[PDB]
Image: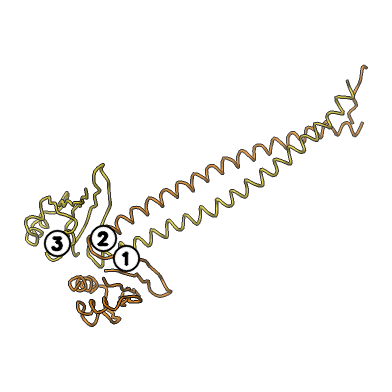
Chain colours: A yellow, B orange
Amino acid sequence: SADLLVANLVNENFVLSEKLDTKATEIKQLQKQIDSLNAQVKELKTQTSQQAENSEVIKDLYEYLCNVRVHKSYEDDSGLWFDISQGTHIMDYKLGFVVTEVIYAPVLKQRSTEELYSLQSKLPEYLFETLSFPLSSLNQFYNKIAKSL
Amino acid sequence: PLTVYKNSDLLVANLVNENFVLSEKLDTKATEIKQLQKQIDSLNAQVKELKTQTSQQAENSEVIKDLYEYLCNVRVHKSYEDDSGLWFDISQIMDYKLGFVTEVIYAPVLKQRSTEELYSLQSKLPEYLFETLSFPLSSLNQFYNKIAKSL
């Protein structure tokens, strides 16, 4: 009973050493995965950021070339909306899209009255009231506002 | 120097001592493993979240690109930066490129075009829009308008 038990401790020391070597492999394997993930993560971070730079330039281009900038976009169940600031250094408004059809909508949440009359002198009455036209007419709209500004 | 007793040495003493050391060396690895497994999971979330945000922002940019096309009849295909100056291909149908070095450079792009069009276009477009040009940025919008009016 005394010898048997102590001779088995050898058996236990072996089992430990194998179970232990099998862990040293699972460990090396995770370290590799981590390193892989790190590379990938960094390259994904540059592509997503550097890409922001591109988009800015383009936004910036359109602004210099069309004197019009698109601020944002939402989608309230039915229809997406984009704020817009058009003019030369200006009339803010929004456009909604719901066959296809469009919705104009002057946006003057904030505007020093002096401007609001400067604008009323340059802009045809109707551009101060919500409207609705087919998409085909959009570009034509755009032109009308540019010509008046 | 340990020594057992039946009822009722160096090597035997190394067995127990050695059995302990193995049990600790093995448990301390089981913690380094859990810590690594956690780190891996955390890193995975990062990759997945970055993939959605990029696929989502791309979506926005596509919408806007599509908007501008419907509103300005003009689309900006790409952008390069060859040491000095960046370039954008444009399709407004007349394709051309614009270079920025402030000052600008126009450049008709007809790498491929069925001749029938190339004369359709020559009838609508003032001679000079078929030759490279150069103007200040302030004049750009004015340029754009001239091309739209003719097309």
Please give the chain letter of the residue carrying mark 2: B
Secondary structure beneath label 3:
helix
Q: Amino acid at mark 1?
A: Val
> Does residue A130 lie above or below B30 as drawn?
below
> Which residue is denoted by mark 2 in the rendering?
B68
Please give the chain letter of the residue carrying mark 3: A
- Whether residues under marks 2 and 1 lie with C-beta atoms below 8 angstroms apart, the answer is yes
Q: Amino acid at mark 3?
A: Ile
Quarter assignment of residue A146: bottom left
> Does residue A37 lie above or below A140 as drawn?
above
Q: Amino acid at mark 2?
A: Tyr
Q: On the rendered structure, is B80 left or right of B146? A: right
The numbered mark at residue A148 is: none
Badge 2: few (under 14), some or many (20 or more) residues near its Cα, within 10 Å? many
> Which residue is denoted by mark 3 in the rendering?
A145
Residue closer to the observer: A97 or B20: A97
- CA–CA distance in space, label 3 to label 1: 23 Å
